Length: 132
Image (cartoon, rainbow, N blue to C red):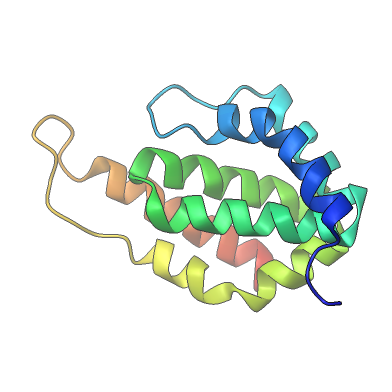
Protein backbone atom coordinates (compact mmCIF):
# COMPACT_ATOMS: atom_id res chain seq x y z
CA UNK A 1 0.00 0.00 0.00
CA UNK A 2 2.08 2.87 -1.32
CA UNK A 3 -0.67 5.60 -1.05
CA UNK A 4 -1.00 7.58 2.15
CA UNK A 5 -2.80 5.60 4.90
CA UNK A 6 -6.43 6.65 5.38
CA UNK A 7 -5.55 7.74 8.92
CA UNK A 8 -3.08 10.24 7.44
CA UNK A 9 -5.65 11.48 4.93
CA UNK A 10 -8.00 12.17 7.85
CA UNK A 11 -5.42 13.88 10.05
CA UNK A 12 -4.40 16.01 7.09
CA UNK A 13 -8.01 17.09 6.54
CA UNK A 14 -7.89 18.42 10.11
CA UNK A 15 -4.79 20.49 9.22
CA UNK A 16 -6.36 22.13 6.15
CA UNK A 17 -7.29 25.35 8.05
CA UNK A 18 -3.55 25.96 8.63
CA UNK A 19 -2.72 25.38 4.98
CA UNK A 20 -5.66 27.32 3.55
CA UNK A 21 -4.71 30.37 5.62
CA UNK A 22 -1.04 30.07 4.62
CA UNK A 23 -1.56 29.76 0.84
CA UNK A 24 -4.56 31.99 0.09
CA UNK A 25 -4.27 33.43 -3.42
CA UNK A 26 -4.03 37.07 -2.36
CA UNK A 27 -1.44 39.74 -1.57
CA UNK A 28 -1.60 39.47 2.26
CA UNK A 29 1.59 37.68 3.41
CA UNK A 30 1.48 34.33 5.16
CA UNK A 31 1.77 34.85 8.95
CA UNK A 32 5.16 33.81 10.30
CA UNK A 33 3.78 31.32 12.81
CA UNK A 34 2.26 29.10 10.09
CA UNK A 35 5.65 28.09 8.67
CA UNK A 36 6.65 26.02 11.70
CA UNK A 37 3.09 24.67 11.86
CA UNK A 38 3.50 23.38 8.31
CA UNK A 39 6.91 21.88 9.05
CA UNK A 40 5.36 19.99 11.96
CA UNK A 41 2.78 18.49 9.58
CA UNK A 42 5.58 17.06 7.45
CA UNK A 43 7.14 15.41 10.52
CA UNK A 44 3.91 13.65 11.59
CA UNK A 45 4.39 10.68 9.25
CA UNK A 46 5.42 9.78 5.71
CA UNK A 47 1.73 9.75 4.79
CA UNK A 48 1.29 13.27 6.14
CA UNK A 49 4.25 14.40 4.04
CA UNK A 50 2.68 12.87 0.93
CA UNK A 51 -0.66 14.62 1.54
CA UNK A 52 1.17 17.90 2.19
CA UNK A 53 3.13 17.61 -1.07
CA UNK A 54 -0.05 16.92 -3.06
CA UNK A 55 -1.63 20.07 -1.62
CA UNK A 56 1.36 22.35 -2.11
CA UNK A 57 2.17 21.21 -5.65
CA UNK A 58 -1.48 21.56 -6.64
CA UNK A 59 -1.53 25.14 -5.36
CA UNK A 60 1.85 25.92 -6.95
CA UNK A 61 0.64 24.81 -10.36
CA UNK A 62 -2.88 26.29 -10.19
CA UNK A 63 -2.67 29.55 -8.21
CA UNK A 64 -2.02 33.03 -9.53
CA UNK A 65 1.38 34.51 -8.76
CA UNK A 66 0.31 35.46 -5.24
CA UNK A 67 -0.40 31.89 -4.16
CA UNK A 68 2.59 30.53 -6.08
CA UNK A 69 4.84 32.89 -4.13
CA UNK A 70 3.43 31.73 -0.79
CA UNK A 71 3.91 28.07 -1.71
CA UNK A 72 7.50 28.71 -2.81
CA UNK A 73 8.28 30.44 0.50
CA UNK A 74 6.74 27.51 2.40
CA UNK A 75 8.77 25.00 0.38
CA UNK A 76 12.01 26.89 1.04
CA UNK A 77 11.23 26.90 4.78
CA UNK A 78 10.62 23.14 4.60
CA UNK A 79 14.13 22.66 3.16
CA UNK A 80 15.48 23.81 6.54
CA UNK A 81 12.73 22.62 8.91
CA UNK A 82 10.72 19.84 7.24
CA UNK A 83 11.09 16.08 7.31
CA UNK A 84 13.78 14.33 5.28
CA UNK A 85 11.04 12.25 3.65
CA UNK A 86 9.22 15.38 2.49
CA UNK A 87 12.40 16.65 0.91
CA UNK A 88 12.96 13.32 -0.88
CA UNK A 89 9.50 13.46 -2.44
CA UNK A 90 9.85 17.15 -3.32
CA UNK A 91 13.10 16.30 -5.09
CA UNK A 92 11.22 13.70 -7.13
CA UNK A 93 8.88 16.46 -8.31
CA UNK A 94 11.64 18.93 -9.31
CA UNK A 95 9.86 19.49 -12.63
CA UNK A 96 7.34 21.68 -10.77
CA UNK A 97 10.15 23.85 -9.38
CA UNK A 98 11.63 24.35 -12.84
CA UNK A 99 8.14 25.27 -14.08
CA UNK A 100 7.78 27.91 -11.35
CA UNK A 101 11.20 29.36 -12.18
CA UNK A 102 9.88 29.79 -15.75
CA UNK A 103 6.60 31.51 -14.76
CA UNK A 104 5.82 34.23 -17.30
CA UNK A 105 2.78 36.00 -18.69
CA UNK A 106 1.23 39.29 -19.73
CA UNK A 107 2.06 42.34 -17.59
CA UNK A 108 -0.30 43.52 -14.88
CA UNK A 109 -1.89 46.95 -15.40
CA UNK A 110 -0.61 48.26 -12.05
CA UNK A 111 2.43 46.18 -11.14
CA UNK A 112 3.79 45.26 -14.57
CA UNK A 113 5.93 42.17 -14.45
CA UNK A 114 6.95 42.42 -10.79
CA UNK A 115 4.88 39.47 -9.54
CA UNK A 116 6.32 37.20 -12.22
CA UNK A 117 9.79 38.38 -11.23
CA UNK A 118 9.20 37.66 -7.55
CA UNK A 119 7.85 34.19 -8.29
CA UNK A 120 10.82 33.30 -10.49
CA UNK A 121 13.35 34.55 -7.94
CA UNK A 122 11.66 32.58 -5.15
CA UNK A 123 11.80 29.44 -7.30
CA UNK A 124 15.49 30.06 -8.06
CA UNK A 125 16.07 30.42 -4.32
CA UNK A 126 14.27 27.14 -3.65
CA UNK A 127 16.22 25.40 -6.42
CA UNK A 128 19.60 26.61 -5.16
CA UNK A 129 18.84 25.10 -1.76
CA UNK A 130 17.07 21.90 -2.84
CA UNK A 131 19.25 20.99 -5.84
CA UNK A 132 22.71 21.78 -4.39
